[PDB]
Amino acid sequence: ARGPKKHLKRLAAPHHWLLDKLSGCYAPRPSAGPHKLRESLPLIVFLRNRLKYALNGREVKAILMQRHVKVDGKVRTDTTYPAGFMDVITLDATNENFRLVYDVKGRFAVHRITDEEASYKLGKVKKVQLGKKGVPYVVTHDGRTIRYPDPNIKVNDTVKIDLASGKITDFIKFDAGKLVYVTGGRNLGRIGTIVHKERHDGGFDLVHIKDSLDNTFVTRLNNVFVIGEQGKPYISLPKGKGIKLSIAEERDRRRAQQGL
Amino acid sequence: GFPMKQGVLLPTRIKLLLTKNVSCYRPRRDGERKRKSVRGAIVGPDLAVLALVIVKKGEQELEGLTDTTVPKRLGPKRANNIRKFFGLSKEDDVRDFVIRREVTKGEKTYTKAPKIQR
Amino acid sequence: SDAVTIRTRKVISNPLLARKQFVVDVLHPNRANVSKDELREKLAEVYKAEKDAVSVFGFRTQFGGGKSVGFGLVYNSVAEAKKFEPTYRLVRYGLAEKVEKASRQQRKQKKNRDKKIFGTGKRLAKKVARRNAD
Amino acid sequence: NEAQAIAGDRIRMFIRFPKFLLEKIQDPKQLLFAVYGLLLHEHKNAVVNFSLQRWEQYDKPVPSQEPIVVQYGVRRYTIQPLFSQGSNSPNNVHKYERFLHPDTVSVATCIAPVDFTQSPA
Amino acid sequence: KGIVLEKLGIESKQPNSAIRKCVRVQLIKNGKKVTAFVPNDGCLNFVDENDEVLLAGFGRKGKAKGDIPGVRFKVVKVSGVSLLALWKEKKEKPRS
Amino acid sequence: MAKVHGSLARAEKPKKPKGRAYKRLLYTRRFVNVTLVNGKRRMNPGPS
Amino acid sequence: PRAPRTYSKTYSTPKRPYESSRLDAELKLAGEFGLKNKKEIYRISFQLSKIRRAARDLLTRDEKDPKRLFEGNALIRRLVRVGVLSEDKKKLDYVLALKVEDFLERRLQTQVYKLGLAKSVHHARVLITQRHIAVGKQIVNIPSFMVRLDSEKHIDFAPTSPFGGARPGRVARRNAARKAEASGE
Amino acid sequence: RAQRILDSIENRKLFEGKNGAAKIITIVPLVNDLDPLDILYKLLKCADDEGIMVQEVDSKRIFNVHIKKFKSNLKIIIPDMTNFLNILDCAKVADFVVFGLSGVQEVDEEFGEQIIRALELQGIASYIGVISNLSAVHEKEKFQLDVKQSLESYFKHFFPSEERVYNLEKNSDALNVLRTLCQRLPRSINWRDNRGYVVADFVDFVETSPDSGDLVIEGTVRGIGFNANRLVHIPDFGDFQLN
RNA sequence: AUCUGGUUGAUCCUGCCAGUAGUCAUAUGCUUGUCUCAAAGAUUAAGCCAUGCAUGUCUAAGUAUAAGCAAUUUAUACAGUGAAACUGCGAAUGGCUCAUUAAAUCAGUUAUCGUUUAUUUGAUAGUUACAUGGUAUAACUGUGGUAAUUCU
RNA sequence: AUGGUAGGAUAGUGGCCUACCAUGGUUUCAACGGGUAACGGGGAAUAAGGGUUCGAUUCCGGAGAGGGAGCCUGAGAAACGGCUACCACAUCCAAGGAAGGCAGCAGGCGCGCAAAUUACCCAAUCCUAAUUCAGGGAGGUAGUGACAAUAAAUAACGAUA
Ligand SMILES: [Mg+2]
Ligand SMILES: [Mg+2]
Ligand SMILES: [Mg+2]
Ligand SMILES: [Mg+2]
Ligand SMILES: [Mg+2]
Ligand SMILES: [Mg+2]
Ligand SMILES: [Mg+2]
Ligand SMILES: [Mg+2]
Ligand SMILES: [Mg+2]
Ligand SMILES: [Mg+2]
Ligand SMILES: [Mg+2]
Ligand SMILES: [Mg+2]
Ligand SMILES: [Mg+2]
Ligand SMILES: [Mg+2]
Ligand SMILES: [Mg+2]
Ligand SMILES: [Mg+2]
Ligand SMILES: [Mg+2]
Ligand SMILES: [Mg+2]
Ligand SMILES: [Mg+2]
Ligand SMILES: [Mg+2]
Ligand SMILES: [Mg+2]
Ligand SMILES: [Mg+2]
C-alpha cells in the first residue's frame, strides 16, 4: 500500500457482522466515525441483513436520502457510517427506536426501545485530561469529548448522556459489585457482577466477574462497560438477559420450545 | 511550429523543463513539468511567423487594422466593475446600468443579463 | 383441473418505502408456471392497489412442478412505484421505456475521443476547415 | 555453401529452351509456373530404391512389370518397378516377389533419376 | 519435444535379442541429444527423418551380461500425432 | 476407419447391456447360475 | 477474488486392487441391492469410515464430559433419524459395530421394492429415475435418497405420473391415437 | 535467450511485409459445389478493401495482394478442379494449404478424401481448415455448432495438429484466420526447401537461335537458393539448362 | 496400523529393484450423453508488445451573457436545465506478478512518556470603505504556425 | 565497524550523517561467506501415532511496474495507465523533429510438455466524486474449458414356448 486503504474484501470482514460469503466480492468497508473499524456496524448491514427493510445496496441508500434513519438524534446519510456500540437508531416512519447491544453469542442484536429510553445513551469514559484554558474534558468511548464534567469522575466510569444537549446526567463509580457488560474479546455477551479488580503494573488489568448464575470469568479492563448497581440497570438488556449457556443445555432449551 | 519564449536569448532552439505558471505549456496533471523544446526570442531567418503589436499609429491607414473594429464581448460582472466602468457613485444602483444582450430565436426576441456578483 | 392458488408468505409492513414486501407461493396443479402479468393483476385486488403499482420477481419453480416460489411487492400508490423501483422492472412492466443508448465500447471510445480535444472544439473545426480549404 | 542468390529476392531467371515447346505454356496469372532447381547429377540416371505401401481400400493387383508413374518430388517418371521385401541381408540380396504384398510395407527398387533429399514418393 | 536425427539399429544380445528400432532425437529447449524408443511399430514407417517428435520417460533396466544399452526415453507423439492412434489406424499423420 | 461426415445426431453379434443391467448379467452369471467345474470356479471355460 | 467454493471427495478407493473375496462381496451387494457401479459401495464405505473415525476419537476420552454427550447424542440422533441404527441399540459402541448393508438398505432404490411399489430392485431403479414415485409432494429421480422415518409413510406414485393418476404417457396416448385412427378408418 | 531471440528474429526477417515478403496461399475446396472465390471474398471482407476485389473479379486467377492491416505481402493461388496433378502442383509449392469444406454436402470419398491423402503424403506446411456453408443450414446457431463440431471431428481425423474448424461467417474469426495467415511461421517441408524454388509471375521469351531461345522468368526465390550451374526442373516440361 | 514377484541345486537372512494406493499436482493419449459447481500464460522469457478499453466527478447549496435549448408565465441584476472552462476532490484505492530478499519479509506478541495523521465524529475562537476592497486569467471572439503530439 | 559526546537532518528516536574521542561488536549454542529453480503466513497433499513433501495462485502482510537513480504536486508516492536523465529495446518522420513502457482486461509474437473471448453490463458486491442520478475490464454475466468436485441415462416388465 501507499496510503489509506479504501476497500474491504468479503473474507476479511469481521465475522460478527455475519455477511454472506457468496453474494459478491466485497464487504462494506465502514468509513471513519465514532467507533473502531472491527467493532462497529455501518448502517447498510443494519438495514439490509439484520432488518430486511431493503433489498439491494441502492435501496438502503434510497432509505438514507429521505432523512429517515437518525443515529444519536442526528440524521446520517452515509451508507458506511460506523454506528457502533450503545447508540440509539431512530426510525421515524416506523415510529420506533433501535439500540445496538450485543447478543449472547458475540454479535450485534436487534432491540426494541421505547421513546423515553431512547432519550439517553450511556458512555464509558475513556480518558480524562485537562484541556486548553485549563478546562477538563472527558472523552467517552465513541469519540465525544464532553467538556466540564463533575470533579469526581475518573477513567473507566460510565456517564449517562442526554442526547439533545450532549451533556452529562449522572455517573457510576467504578467499584466492586456493579453490573458490568463485557465489550469485546472472545468471551463476549455476558453481564454480571464484579467480584474484584485485579491490579497489574505496567501491563493489563484483569477483573473477575461473577454472573447471576454464579460463573466467574476474567476479562481485561479494556473490555468492561459499566451498566449499574445490583439488579437495577440503567438500560434494558436483550433477550437471554446477558447470561451465556453451555451448548448442551442450549439445545435443551431449544428442544423445550416445540409443542405444535 | 515551435513558439518563441520571452526570456531565452539565443537564435537557436533549447529544450527546457517548463512549469505551471508560464507560457508554452499547460500541465495536464497537477504540478506537472515536461521537457519541451522551445525556440529563442532572438529573431533570425528561421521564423515562419513573427507577430507584432501596434504601439504608435502612423500616417497611412490600414484596411483590416485601422478601419475595422470589433466590440468587446462580455460586459463587467462585479458591482464595483459596473461602478468604475460607468463612473457611478457609491449610492448609485448598479441594477439599471447593466449591459443587456438581445438574442433572437424564431419570432421571440429575448434579452439576457449577467448575474451580478459582490 | 387447474386452481391457481396464491398465498402470500411472511408479509411485513415497510413504512419506510410506502410498500409491503412478502414471498409469493403459488400452487398450480397441471399448470406450467403462472405469468408475472397474471399474478400481478391477481395480487392487485387482493392487496387493493393498482395493477401498475405492484411488482413480482425472482420466481423459482420447484422440482417436480405444480409449485413456484417468488418474492412479491405491493406499493400503496403508483407514484411510489415510479419512484422506488429499479428501472429494469419498470421497463419490464411497460411503465418505462428502454432508453436506446449505444453499447459500452463506443461509449468509452467517444469519451476518449472527447477527452482528446480541449475547449469547445469548433475553433479547431473552423481551423481544420480553413486548413483543408488551403 | 556456394549458393549465389539467397532466398527472398526478386530474380530474373533465364533458361535455355527449345522453340517447339512454346505452344504448351500458359498465362502465368491464369496458371501457375513453378520453377524447381535440381542438385548435382540429378539428371544423371542410376539404380535407386523406393519404399512402397499400398493405399487403403485398394485391393487391385499390381505386378512387377507394368508401367506405373512415380510422383517423387516434382518429376514424374513411368517405371516397371521390381517388388521385394526389405529384410536386411549380410550379402545384400533380397527376394523378388511377383506382386505387391497386401499386408506390410514392401520395397521397390528400379532404374530412375536420383533424388538427394529423401522426398516422399 | 524433439527433432529426430537418425535411425539406430542397435543389436542387443543376451538374454533376448531385441531388434532395436529406435530413433536418435535432438531436443529443442537445451540442444543435447538423447536416444529414444519407438513403441508398438513393427516397421517404424511413421517416425521418418526430420519429423518433430515429443519424448517421454521410460524406466527400462539395461543388463550387464548382454551389453544391452540404457535407453530412457520413449515417443508419445510424432508430427503432432499420437503414435497410439497411428498404430490403431484411427487418425492420420502429415508427413512433414 | 474414417467416419463419413453424416455423424449429425440432431436433425453382427447382438449388443451388450451396459450400466446396471451389466451388473445384473454378472450377478446371474456368477451366483444365480453357478457353473460347477471340477470343484473350482472356472471363469471362461473352453471345450471340456 | 471470491470465496473459493469448497469441494471434497466422497468415495475412497480400496488399497489393494485385486482380491477375490472383496470383489465377490461387492458383486453380491451390487447385484442384490441393485446398484450400478462399485462407486456406490465406495461412497458408503467412506461414510462408514467417517462415522467410525468420529466414534473412535469420541470413545478414547473420559465419560461424562459434555463434549462426549454432545457429539455422541447428536450423532446417534442423526443416525436414528435415518433408521440405520435401530432404536433398541442406542449406545455409541453399537454405532461403531455397524456395517455397509445397514446404510445400504435405506435407499429409495431398495425401499420402493420392499414397500411393494415395484416388481424388482432394478424395477424400483427405473420407477425412481423416470420421475414416477414421490416422497410425499416431491418428485425424485434419485435412488440414493436415504429415506427417513417420517418420510417412509408418505411414499407413493407421483400425481404427475401415469401410475399415480392423470393422463397416460406418450407411448399410451400414441398407441391410443393409433387404434383411434385404425377404428376411424 | 539473447541469441535465441536473435535467430528467431533472423528467421522472421524473411517476411518483411513492406518489400521483401512472399506468402503463398492455396485454397482448395473438398466438394464439387463450392466456388473458391467466395472463400476469397469472405476472407478479405475483414481487410475492408473493395477495389482489390473489383480488380479481382473480371478475368484473373493469380493475385498479389498487399494488406496494410498487418503489413504483409500475399500471393494466392487458385487450382483448376479439372486436373488432380494441377492441385498437387498448387499445394506442393504453397507455404499455406487452406482446405474448403461444405456444411451442406458431405465431402467425397471418391474425390476429396484422396485430395486429403495425396496432399498429406506429398507434404503439407502449416494448414488452415475452414467452412463457408454454415449459413445455408438452419439459422439457429445451436444447430450450427453441432455442424461445426462434426467438421471438427472430421478434420481432426486427418489433421491432428489443429483442432478448430474456423468460420468465415464470423467477422472476428475471419480476423483470426487472416491474422494466422499473415503472422505465423509456416513449417518447412524438407525436400523442397533444400533445393530452392521460384514461383513465376511473368513469363517472356528471348529468341537466340531459330531452334531454341531464352525464357524470361520474373519471380521471388524461395528455399536454399539457385546456382547458375545446377539444372532446373519444370513440371510437365522436364529438365533444362541455365543461361 | 496389511504387503508381494526377483540372487540359489534347494533353504533361511541382509539388501535394493519392480509391482500397489493417493495427490483438491502437472502434461499427454483414447473416449465422451446429462445436472450443479469450477481452476484456467505461475513453472520457461519479471521476454517483446499492434490496436481498443481500464479515472474521472455537479448537488436546492463555489463560478453561467454558451451569440446552446426551452419559452414561460411575476421576475430589467440573475433565478429552468446546461456543452465548455475555472475552482474543490479523487487519481497514493482497486487490478496484476513473484524478479530481488535467509533475522530480510513475515507469524504471534509488545511499545510510541519517540512521531506525522486529507477525511469522518465531538468540542473548540466578544481581544485583529464593512451596506462588503483590489487584480489577473481560463472557457468564449479573432489572427496564426508544422508532416506530425492530449503542441500551442 | 561497536560505543561516548556535541551538532545537522527528519514527521520524529537512532552512526541516519558530520566533527572530536575511546577499541570495541559477533562467533563451534554455527557468526562471516556460498547456494536456493526461497515472497512469508493462514493452508494443501499423504499419514494409527510420530512425521514427510509442497504453499507463484481466491485472505492478510511485503516488493516491483524493462534496469538503476532523481524529484514536483499532495495529508498520503521516491508514484510509473506522473515527470527527468542514463542503459537496453523500439514507433512515425516531409529528416528538422516527436512520442513509448499491457507483471491491468481481452488479444498478438516468442518460449515451452504446459494454460481461454480483441463478447455483454453496472442489474448484483462494493468503491470514488461536488456526490440518488455520473464513472468503475474492480466486479457480475455469457463464450472456450474431461484441471478438479457432487448426483447419475445406456433400459424395466410381462406372457408364450
Ligand atoms: Mg494495492
Ligand atoms: Mg482477544
Ligand atoms: Mg518401488
Ligand atoms: Mg512468465
Ligand atoms: Mg442547477
Ligand atoms: Mg470536524
Ligand atoms: Mg543528539
Ligand atoms: Mg566520523
Ligand atoms: Mg524466486
Ligand atoms: Mg504464497
Ligand atoms: Mg517462480
Ligand atoms: Mg493469475
Ligand atoms: Mg510500490
Ligand atoms: Mg515486459
Ligand atoms: Mg488528492
Ligand atoms: Mg519508478
Ligand atoms: Mg499503479
Ligand atoms: Mg501498463
Ligand atoms: Mg494482459
Ligand atoms: Mg477480472
Ligand atoms: Mg456507475
Ligand atoms: Mg472433471
Image (spheres, coloured by chain):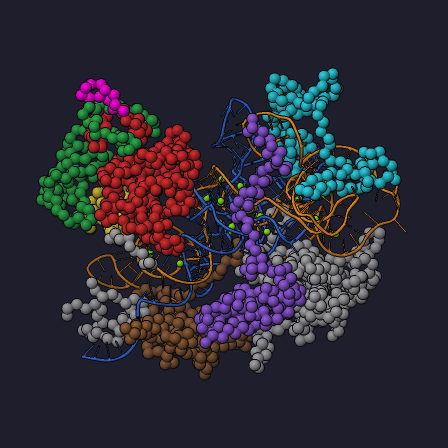
Chain colours: B cyan, C purple, D green, E yellow, G brown, H red, I orange, J blue
Residue G139 against residue I65 in the figure, above or below: below
Please give the name of the residue rendered at 32% of the width and 67% of the height, measured from the top-left corner: F19
Residue I111 against residue H234 in the figure, above or below: below
The region drawn magenta spans H204-215
Residue H218 belongs to the span the image colors magenta: no
Quarter containing the N terminus of chain E: top left
Answer with left or right where residue G109 lies relative to residue C35. Answer: left
* Nearest the eye: A241 or J93: J93
Please give the name of the residue rendered at 48% of the width and 68% of the height, measured from the top-left corner: C33
Answer with left or right where residue H76 lies relative to residue A116. Answer: left
Residue H212 belongs to the span the image colors magenta: yes
Q: Position of residue E53 (x, y in %)?
A: 31, 44
* Nearest the eye: G177 or C87: G177
Answer with left or right where residue H17 lies relative to residue B117. Answer: left
Residue H32 against residue B25 in the figure, above or below: below
Q: Position of residue H236 (x, y in %)?
A: 20, 32
Q: Position of residue C69 (x, y in %)?
A: 52, 69
Answer with left or right where residue J142 lies relative to residue A206. Answer: left
